[PDB]
Length: 116
Image (cartoon, rainbow, N blue to C red; front, side):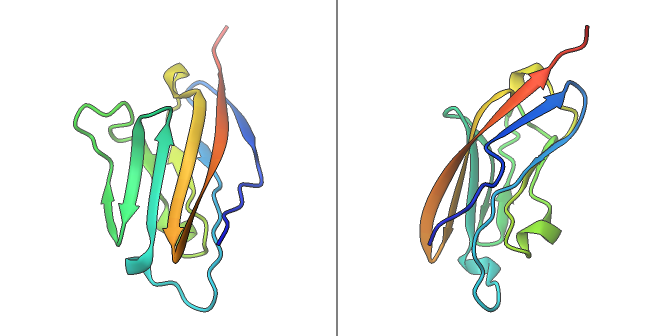
C-alpha cells in the first residue's frame, strides 16, 4: 500500500482556491468505512475523514470553513484537500496521511503569492 502525490508543490495566488491531489489505490470497490484520511500542516490538523466521519476541528481552527474533502474525488481514490480563499498563513508543508488496509504519507508544499 502506497499513496502517490504527482505534484510535489503548488504555487497559488492570495484569494484563489487550491486542490492538492493525494491518490490511493482502490482494488475493486471502495469501502468508506475502511478509509481514514488526515491532512496536517506543520503539526496542525486541517481536516480528517475517519470511517465516514469528517471533522474540520473548527474549534478555533485556522481553516474553520475553508477546507474540504470533495467526495466525488474520494470515491475515485483521490483524497484531495480543497482550500478556498487562500491566505498567506496557508503556505507551508502539508502532510497527507491515508489508511486503507495499510498506511502511508506524502508531504506537499504550498506557496502563496501576495498582492502587490
